[PDB]
Image (cartoon, rainbow over all chains, first blue to last red; front, top):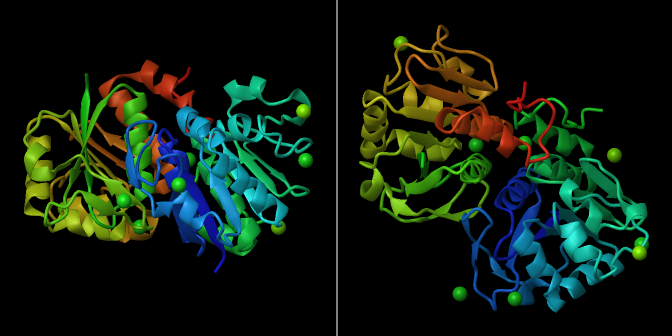
Length: 195
Length: 195
Ligand SMILES: [Cl-]
Ligand SMILES: [Cl-]
Ligand SMILES: [Cl-]
Ligand SMILES: [Cl-]
Ligand SMILES: [Cl-]
Ligand SMILES: [Mg+2]
Ligand SMILES: [Mg+2]
Ligand SMILES: [Mg+2]
């Protein structure tokens, strides 16, 4: 199967993390969750208090051959990612080895921009953090797929379905993305991959 | 200081549970999560494998004065609810005492219909299970609010935002629902409480 490494830190946005995980599993993707910036503790208290148990510490899975690394948002979770040298070097390694980096909400501006990971990539993120993304790189769009650098970005809790579906499309294919979308009772406006 | 009791079981649908909890917290509603696991275990494995910690076993919080009891879906989570005499008694007590019952996805057909808790009233649920909701009660709407019996129902993972926003309306009101909605970057097909 295709596989995904979903990172979690104290203060990660729980809808973004959980909805993404759920959709990837529905798509037949094996998902591992990794605890970041917790010195190995697998208990992760998210941004609105939801408490998740991660599968493993990042340091034990960072060298795995996952097809995508996923960075949920949440202000404080994204700061933890930014300030983790292991997280940043893992993101860089996924990219250099031809794999996908996927980031939502505050993660693009907080993690990718300060570390100059994708200096000329196109990206989106949470609208109120537009001023944290260099102006020439910013698109205000529910999902942005920059195929040149294999960078997938998205905007907020309410775009987590759109984000997860595009990961499925990229890793498994359009037909599987449509199958998953069809299970959800999605709002009008969200792309369902039928065409 | 409105409050919500969100029930969780092995096999609950994690998007439905977590997105609902998230939105209620954003709305200033005090949330308590209650495990309906038969042994009282609080470390719940949800339908796609997300590991979610409940705050308390149902028996320790069921008699609380929460304004709403929330039943997430997930095929096996809803079966656990149906087969828990304490859960069913608690739902009945919320209803008889003039409080709100909120249920999504499989929870209406699996829990409410077999126990005949709402013999009169409109309801929805996951559309593949529509033939398990009595025909005179069924509506095919993203959210159904029947104020006559204080029953809120909704259809699936993709309607979790609509569901959570309606709980906010019912507990805190339209202004707060609009405020929360405006945070999410949600899709155009979800009612946003602005006129
Ligand atoms: Cl441990
Ligand atoms: Cl670690
Ligand atoms: Cl670049
Ligand atoms: Cl959504
Ligand atoms: Cl399910
Ligand atoms: Mg620059
Ligand atoms: Mg394609
Ligand atoms: Mg009847």
